[PDB]
Image: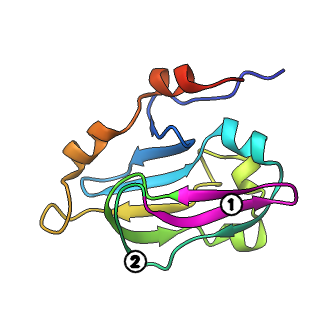
Amino acid sequence: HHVSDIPSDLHYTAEHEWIRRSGDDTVRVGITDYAQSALGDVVFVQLPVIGTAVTAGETFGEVESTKSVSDLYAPISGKVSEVNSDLDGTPQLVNSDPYGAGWLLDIQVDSSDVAALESALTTLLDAEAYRGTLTE
């Protein structure tokens, strides 16, 4: 049994997404090591369109192995500002590198339209709290 990687520098949701603050107004989002391992080899990733306004907790996609499908949720409100085009051809990046090249999308927040990031991040789990949720 491998112990799943949970980078200390990320935030998480209980539903096994990670959130990296990539800029003042941007988070990058993927699924955790635990999630990718549980799902199985990702054969498909449905991500939302760049520009899509998302609200926290909203289903905006799905990640799919041959055995399993899992909804992807917006961990924060904002707008999808990037999606990882690599996953079209190489979806198993999610499995091989869940926190790196396997990232799914970015959500950009404007303070104006949605919660400032500082605040948005307060709904999210830290690495330790995420680990705490896991039955691994």
Q: Which residues are magenta?
A: 58-72
Disc 2: CA contacts within 10 A as few (<14), some (14-19) or many (>=20): few
Query: In the image, what residue type sits under mark 1?
Result: Val
Type of amino acid at the residue the image marks with label 2: Thr
- Give residue 129's position: percent from left, percent from top: 46, 23
The percent coordinates of residue 32 (x first, y second) are 61, 41
**Location of residue 72 in the rendering, given as x and y in whole percent from the top left corner:** 56, 58
Q: Quadrant of residue 51?
A: bottom left
Q: Residue visible at 27% across and 37% down?
A: 122
Q: Is residue 102 above or below residue 43?
A: above
SS at mark 2 in the image: loop
Quarter of the image where the C terminus is located: top right
Our reading of the magenta stretch's main secondary structure is strand
**Residue denoted by label 2:** 52
Q: Position of residue 45 (x, y in %)?
A: 68, 67
Residue lying furthest right in this view?
66
Q: Residue at x 56, y 23 (%)?
A: 131
Instruction: Please give the label number shown on residue 63.
Output: 1
In this rendering, the answer to whether 114 lies above or below 41 is: below
The residues tagged by marks 1 and 2 sit, at their Cα atoms, a distance apart of 18 Å
Q: Is residue 121 magenta?
A: no
Image side of residue 109 versus residue 131, left or right:
left
Circle 1 crowding by C-alpha within 10 Å: few under 14, some 14–19, many from 20: many
Q: Quadrant of residue 56?
A: bottom left
